Image (tube, helix red, strand yellow):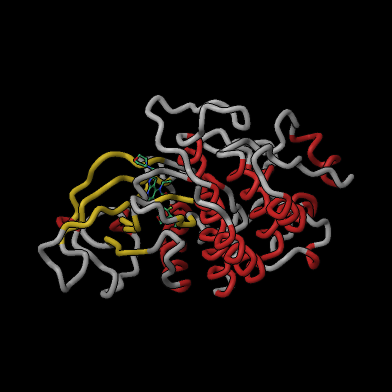
Amino acid sequence: GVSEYELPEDPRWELPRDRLVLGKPLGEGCFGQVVLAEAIGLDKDKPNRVTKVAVKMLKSDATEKDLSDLISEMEMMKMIGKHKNIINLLGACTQDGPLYVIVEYASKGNLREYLQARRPPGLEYSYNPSHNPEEQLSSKDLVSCAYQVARGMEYLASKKCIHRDLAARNVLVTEDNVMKIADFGLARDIHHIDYYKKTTNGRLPVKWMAPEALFDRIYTHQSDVWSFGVLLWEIFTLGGSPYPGVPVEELFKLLKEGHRMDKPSNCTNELYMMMRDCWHAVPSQRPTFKQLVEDLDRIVALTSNQ
Ligand SMILES: CCN1C(=O)N(c2c(F)c(OC)cc(OC)c2F)Cc2cnc3[nH]c(CN4CCOCC4)cc3c21
């Protein structure tokens, strides 16, 4: 029972449950549930204002370890602090019920789904799967997505945070088209990892791992930079799947032999070189997120929004 555990109450973050008006499901995961909610008076200055938020909670079959992870993720987000380009912590409910972790809500879904819905019916992209498509994104908008994500990672890096699974599905898009990085404070599994098991959404996270993380389970900022390269490829394929036609068992040998993904049809040479630099075999030779932010900042200014 949740009453049988000692939940860490933080007065600065604590919100009464009856201030939340729970709504539609936002998605699932390992053992966590996330719902949409309306928070009444999230800010003490405006107690009569409503704010759309996302609420994460434990499922019916959650164990003691799951609770420990959810708390761990919450306290981690506290320590890392706030940034525009990450999913921020807004509050928590630790009393009179199950643990609720309140975070920012992104209404336009993850980056893969966001981009796929805005795929032009053209030659250079796969088909738009959305039955209700949205307006095509400009070239500047695409580089802008990359910059924002890189900026968020640059911040997380400065807070000694290693994401270990940076991907398009782990980036969320707000109503104002702001890119926000998700799941950056997840507890690392203490057991060895299944290279072949899919996520609840059918994704193979193996395809984002750097070679050193893949072969020796070594995770650094440099390995995140590798992942950012794969994300860059995802953006300019508008939500494409990494290494098309390549099975996981063959991905081990291919990567070691120096094989990398081809440049997407709609992608500048300069942006592809950036992917390749991120995909450098030697971790120390990959660019830092600081350098990535500086380049992408320059490229955004020079990229046409026409
Ligand atoms: C992918 C599910 N999800 C989360 O997992 N969130 C989340 C969270 F609850 C959380 O609790 C600690 C930590 C996170 O990373 C820091 C999160 F990203 C916050 C979060 C915020 N907005 C979201 N929007 C969506 C997708 N919806 C689906 C249908 O409604 C429109 C879009 C998922 C989602 C969402």
Residue 102 rendering spot, x and y as whole percentages: 32, 58
Horizontally, is 248 left or right of 127 in the view? Answer: right
The total number of labels drawn is: 0
Horizontally, is 206 left or right of 173 in the view? Answer: right
The image quadrant that residue 241 belongs to is: top right
30 relative to 191, above or below: above
The residue at 34%/46% (across/down) is 107
39 relative to 250, above or below: below
The residue at 70%/32% (across/down) is 244
Residue 68 rendering spot, x and y as whole percentages: 45, 59
Of residue 267 and residue 114, the one placed in the foreground of this image is 267
Residue at the right extreme, as displayed: 257
Horizontally, is 80 left or right of 272 in the view? Answer: left
The residue at 54%/65% (across/down) is 151
62 relative to 250, above or below: below
Of residue 119 and residue 260, the one placed in the foreground of this image is 119
175 relative to 184, above or below: above
Residue at the left extreme, as displayed: 48
Residue 147 rendering spot, x and y as whole percentages: 55, 60
Of residue 208 and residue 120, the one placed in the foreground of this image is 120
The image quadrant that residue 219 belongs to is: bottom right
Of residue 12 and residue 116, the one placed in the foreground of this image is 116
Residue 224 rendering spot, x and y as whole percentages: 65, 59
The residue at 45%/74% (across/down) is 79
